[PDB]
Image (cartoon, rainbow, N blue to C red):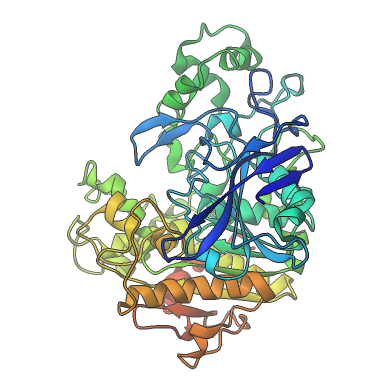
Length: 536
């Protein structure tokens, strides 16, 4: 009464009781790829081999290798390319719309586990939630330029492609409707969605998408190759012999715990002034396979995106930049660094050094007209980092949709500022701070390990239900209007302007509203640095 046939074998899930009270069928750890093990390490994913014996998926699986920062421990397993189905029940005769989730984690960490991405809140509406593991860091994004070596790159993105291909081919038997799939992603997970939207390799595999605080227009979404395959082999303790090819087979020989340990560790150039966020991330592939995700420059891929023909919802939070203070609590006075401003003028502009000098002055006057950056006078830098790192990419994505897509584009802004419920800002950043930070909003969508729940008279509860309602509203009929928006007398309309800005649903403590983006003036300034460069 809880066994399902997948295309590769039989699968038995569990039944359970939400943090709210409702019951739901759960399946966890369903293979969709053969363990990228041994020889297949670093490589594109291949299906699993058929298995005849009913496999237990009543318990969560281990994540793809990484440093789990909540534990401060390396963790994982290489055989972790498994997928997860949550739903109130299985109706193979009433096929429900699918929400498919892709986790974030800077392409370096992340997990599909119900300890950050709890289905309790979302399984109340009538959808099918899906979530899955894809490989991260070097293990998922190593790039060997010799075709001889079979590591083109982007193995993690290809893991996500396969996963989507699986939801299509299987979800029918969990009560899913493979032709009503919404792809949803946060941070790197959002940048991932948008690569699926702009790459032909993920063409028409889904119908709608929600893009959260992440974009192909953020510079951190694409890595440049700078001899990373060897710099890592070296740092791990490699003789120097064999070229890149020879560093690879040493890496195929290394404990993955070592790969992880040394990954981000000894890597970046310091010419990350030229924004290299990470070096095991998405890359333009050196040659073409059938599984290829990124054949050429993303910027150009975007101009002819299959995705421009489907509806999407996109947004982020009001103080995304809070993420960036982390690095600032560890060696402050980097806010007194005198290149603090001039090193946030985007590196790759075809502008002279005098313009660049001039732009960084406009940044001072915007974010710190008269006062000095410091751990106590930080809002200006949080705004700066919010714009540079997240929103300018979101905004370009919105402008580009308005120009070249005749689809609907819905824009949101999360402002929920709670003293206890904004978990990521509170646990991972600082219990001191206010504002809405990168991934705060995920507390209002997913249950997590805290088992925490605001108690129905609190505005936090109003927030929870509002998001859950608009996101599932969109997942169900490509229309984000719902009960909660109604009982504030607002209509979430798709965006229909760029000047003076775009219009978004602003979800605040005190409810919702459909307004001009309130921080437009800042982003005008970022647009203006792009005066000799094409925005989209």
